[PDB]
Image (cartoon, rainbow, N blue to C red; front, top):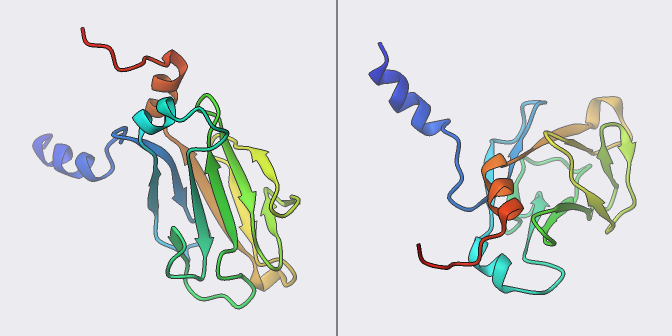
Amino acid sequence: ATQRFLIEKFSQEQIGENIVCRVICTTGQIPIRDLSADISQVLKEKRSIKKVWTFGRNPACDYHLGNISRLSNKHFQILLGEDGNLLLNDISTNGTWLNGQKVEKNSNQLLSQGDEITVGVGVESDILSLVIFINDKFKQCLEQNKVDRIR
């Protein structure tokens, strides 16, 4: 009974193809998704940004939620830049929360491991939480920062 484990493990396998961060809903409302950015572009681009994700009720948004009026089309956005460091940018009409602490809108914050962002604050029964998972594999690549190079 190990072969089957491999198949099941494949779906929930440690991804590191070019993964940036993973979004996981704990309140059971939005389905898990995988956020990612290409390393070549990150190591190549010498700017203060590589790729940013937008989350909200917008079908365009990099993250499609259920349908909560309390949340905006693009409730929040996540940016990826620097030497692998990740940043979280809130962009909600009502506000974005971090572990119960409301952060400044359209503001950059230092991402946290397995962090969680809460949204739709105002009504105890109208708040939705989201958990962010950072890919350890990606961090390993950035930590070493190896420019292409062959053997």
